[PDB]
Amino acid sequence: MSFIFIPTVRTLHQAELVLNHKNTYLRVNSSHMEVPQLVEFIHQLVDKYPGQKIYVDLQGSKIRISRSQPNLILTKDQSVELTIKAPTKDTKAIHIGNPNTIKLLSQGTHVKIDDGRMEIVVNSIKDSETAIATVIKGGELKPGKGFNLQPHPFVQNQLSERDAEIVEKLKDVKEVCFALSFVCVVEEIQDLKKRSNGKYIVAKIEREMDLERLKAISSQCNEIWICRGDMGVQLGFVGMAKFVREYTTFMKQLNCPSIMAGEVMEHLCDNTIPTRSEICYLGNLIADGYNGIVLSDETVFGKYPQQTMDFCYDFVQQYLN
Amino acid sequence: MSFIFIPTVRTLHQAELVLNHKNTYLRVNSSHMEVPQLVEFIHQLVDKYPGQKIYVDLQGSKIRISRSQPNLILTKDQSVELTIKAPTKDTKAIHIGNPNTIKLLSQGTHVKIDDGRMEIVVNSIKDSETAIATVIKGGELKPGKGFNLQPHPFVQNQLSERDAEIVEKLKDVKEVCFALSFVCVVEEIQDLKKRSNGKYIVAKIEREMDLERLKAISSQCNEIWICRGDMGVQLGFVGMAKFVREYTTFMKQLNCPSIMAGEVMEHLCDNTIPTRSEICYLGNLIADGYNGIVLSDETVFGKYPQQTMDFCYDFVQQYLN
């Protein structure tokens, strides 16, 4: 078997529950803990599991509402300010966490907020920190929610100060691999290769991209994850379904392994049996030639991390014979 | 759009919640109510919805533990009697509902009971009503649980007295179509065509079958359902996943439409959003050329019957354009 499994963990205990099998490598979401805690956790894991690669998932280009954003009622048709400034008391603006965000906006850009529970259209750029938008769909704005642009330009996002720091503080741990969220261009991989001293890099594909772009990216990175979580908001459900299928048809043209991610086995977070579509879909992705799966919520949040991991392994093994 | 939707209902209210859209035809599970109630329900529906075909699902060849079976502790390695006799007080036997069952058993036949929670191997046939078996996996035997044979021979099952009655009492309602559970051979379709006066017939495929068998069946029936519920127990999860994929590769050779069934959208029984694998799998089954889906539990038991139906319709429509 060359197929692999990437279960997500955030404790030592979890790691022990999912590491029963070969071809299995931990993912750690660097959103899940503060940088010092991440560094200590990785150091513990590599002491316990020497030489075993660990995928450290960088939140990368992902855009969110600021964590210090005060709750705000946005009303349909109101004008509103979008800004990368830090939140202040009595702000009436939408405050974005990623400071590269203004440069990604243009007149006409739609932004889905909180998976589409709210929607705005950008009217103009006011200054380097601020855009003016119109609310299309209103509701209560909360800290930390998603913020997805349509269209989203294909430009180099520089790493965030936090991700740059993570890379700097982990580049001396031989086992660490980095997964870069929301890759758009090859230059983002090249930058991360340079900063990490040549480490193994995963490009996380969370949007529609043509084959030629992906060929370029695939010649610089070491692995590709198809990340259906955020792809679903970015593209909508039909657009996601279509693009993952199109990707499957041309992935063999890429020079790296392709790993399926995002709710591969979501029904196993809470339930004891996967659904018949989950099961059929996992068989089909083996036969279509995917090289592995990522387990996220199913292991890191789920009530059955060990059983989920063991089910997946047992299913694939039997499938291949 | 020629794709169709077959939601399952058991009340007038449910039927109203799922009939918002074109290309949508009710399924009624004839297990769900007594024959007189079924007959009255169908009469109500066709008064309300004249000329609209209704799929009446016959439980067919399905084998279950008797409903009058007293609870019984089966112990690993015990000998036990399997019988088609009615249950009696103090029976120590496993009592089967379908009286054709003895003829389907042979020395060496395994039977999974209650989806595999218990397992037996048949040692011999004792008499026309009774086989002797050894328990492989024990537990508490309860009325009404499933009973799946491996191997299951390809023979004509005659209809049950109950199904024969249903057919007789419904054959004069022009809208009724019959779905026959667990089809194995063309003769079962021919018989049901004769008894129903030529009605539209669905062969329910709930087992692995070669293409040539299915070509024969498909030339006599009007539609095929791939029924992943019972197929999953019959074949196991890997065997199901493999066979549905193999079926998809040759279904275009069959002369009738192919409809996907069994947990197409199971996560929507209890949850508000389908999983990313549910969504991708539904897109792929459209692109692979399935001609529709059956919704079972999702509409007849689910908390969101209307929303589930409307999601599916809206997804397919957008997919096709």
Image (cartoon, coloured by chain):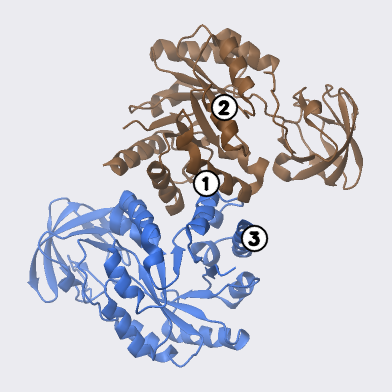
Chain colours: A blue, B brown
Q: Are marks 3 and 1 on the same chain?
A: no
Dot 3 corresponds to which residue? A314
Q: Disc 2: which chain?
A: B
Q: Tell if the residue under mark 2 belongs to the same chain as the one under mark 3.
A: no
Quadrant where the N terminus of chain A sits is: bottom right
The quadrant in which residue A95 appears is bottom left
- Return the x and y of residue A112 as percentages of the image width and height: 25, 57
Query: How dense is the environment of label 1, judged by Cα within 10 Å: few (below 14), some, or many (20 and up)?
Result: some
Query: Foreground residue, B272 or B8?
Result: B8
Q: Position of residue A152 (x, y in %)?
A: 21, 65
User: The residue marked by circle 3 belongs to what chain?
Assistant: A
Residue A132 occupies quadrant: bottom left
Label 1 marks a residue whose chain is B
Q: What residue type is labelled 3?
A: Asp
Q: Does residue B76 appear to the left or right of B234 in the view shown?
A: right
Residue type at mark 2 is Ala
Badges 2 and 3: C-beta atoms under 8 Å apart? no
For label 2, the SS is: helix
The answer to whether one can see residue B160 in this image is yes
Residue B271 % position (x, y): 46, 46
Nearer to us: label 2 or label 3: 2
Find numbered disc 1 in the image and state the secondary structure of the residue it sits on: helix
Q: In this view, does A260 lie above or below B228?
A: below
**Could you say which disc has been placed on residue B216 in the image?**
2
Q: Kindly report which numbered mark, 3 or 1, lies closer to the viewer in this rendering.
A: 1
Task: Say which quarter of the image contains residue B121.
Answer: top right
Q: Which of A157 and B133 is in front in this view?
A: B133
